[PDB]
Image (cartoon, rainbow, N blue to C red; front, top):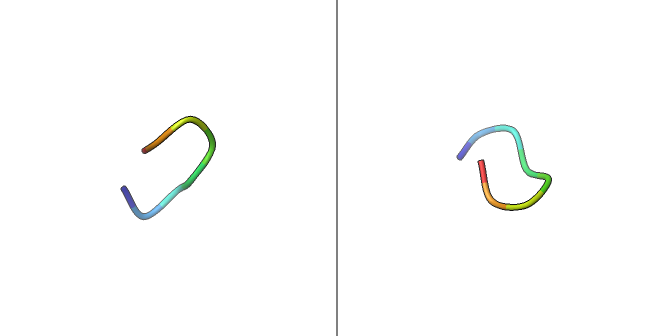
Length: 8
């Protein structure tokens, strides 16, 4: 969350 990638 708030970062992206594989679901951050």
